[PDB]
Image (cartoon, rainbow over all chains, first blue to last red):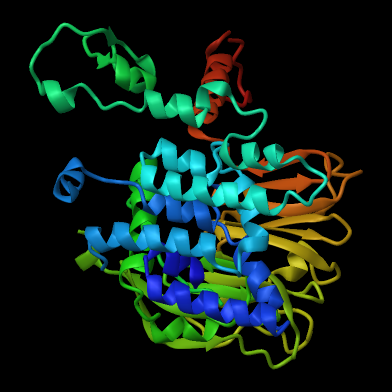
Length: 208
Length: 255
C-alpha cells in the first residue's frame, strides 16, 4: 500500500501513513508493520528511497524549459516532496542509514541513481540527508567517514561509476543541438546495439 | 493481501511484447487503482500455493488445503483485462474433509492430489469429481492401472497432454489426457522407481504437454516427447539403415 502511494506520488497518503507509523513506534504496536514496509522492494532490488528517486527522473527537456492520474508538474513536485518527507520523517531515521547504503540491481545507492538519472534535485536532497545521518551516528565504533562514503559512493565501487565523475560525464546527445545536420565530431560504432559501421553515435552517447 | 491479474500473450510472440503486457498491469496499479472483480475477491485474503489454467476454467490451490475453479474466456474485443470470468466460482466438493497438497490440469479434466496421496479426477464438464463406490480412496478411475491406489502420491505436475506423479517411495507414474487414452499404451507407464532415479529423492516435477522432467536432490532427469529435430535425425537414420543392402523363395516373409 505505502509503496504504491510512493509510486502514485500521493504525498498526502504517504504523510498519513508515516504519521500512523510514528504512532506505531511510540505506542510499541504494529512494529512488524513498520519493519515489513521497510523491507518492501520493487523490481531492480529498489527500496522505497530508490523508488522515489526513479520517480523523480525527468522525461523531457520541454518540462525543464517551462520550469526555467497525476500531472507531470505535480508528479515531479510530489515525488521530490515524498523523498524529502521520508528522509525527514522520524519513522525512518533509524533505518535511513541502511536504506541509503543499500545497493540496487546495478550497485547504485539512491544518491548514485539520482545522479545517473539526472535527478540532480533528488541527488542534492539525498546528499544533504546523508551528511545528517553520518553526523548523527558519530557515537558508533565506525568513523563518520565510513558511513558517509557508503551512502554516497560505497567502497569497492568501480571508480568510473563515481557520482562526481558520472556527473561530469552526463552530457547530452549531440543531436539535441546538431539536429540531423552533419558536423565534424568523433563517432563510434557499437555492435552491441546494432550500430554497425553504416551507423554511429557521438562520443557522449558512447560514454553514457 | 494479494490481487489477481490476468495476462494474455499471442503465440508465437516476443519477450518485449510480454514485458509490455506486464507494464500495462503496473500502469493500472499506479494509475487506475481499480477495484478487483467480485468473482475472485474471496481469494484476496486467501493464500495461494499453486494455480493452473485449463482450456475453459482456471483453478487455484490454497495453502489451507482448499481447491476451486472458475470458467473464463479471452475477449477478442481486447485482443485487437483481456480475460472475463463468470460469476459462478466452484469450490471443490470436499465431502471427505481432506486437504490437498498439489494440483495440475489436463485438457479434459482437472487433477489434484490429497494430503493422503490420493489422486483425484474431475472433468471440466462434470459437477463433481470421480469417486469409486467400491473403493473410497480411489478418486481416479485409472489409478488401478498406474498402481497409484497403493502408493502415496507426494508430488504432481500436468499440462494439457501429459500428467506425471512422484510417490513417497520415489515411484514415477505417467498418464495422458483421455483424448490420447486410446494410444496411451505408447505414452503412459505405471508407477515405477526407475533405476536412473534410484538413489535420489524427487524434489519437484516439471510436466508439460510433451514431456516431464523430475528435479532430484543432486541431478536432473527427464522423459517424454522429443523435439522435432531429433525426431527427424532418428527417422533419417532408420530409413538409411533400411535402404542399405535377395534370396526370395516360396514361404519367405517379405515387405
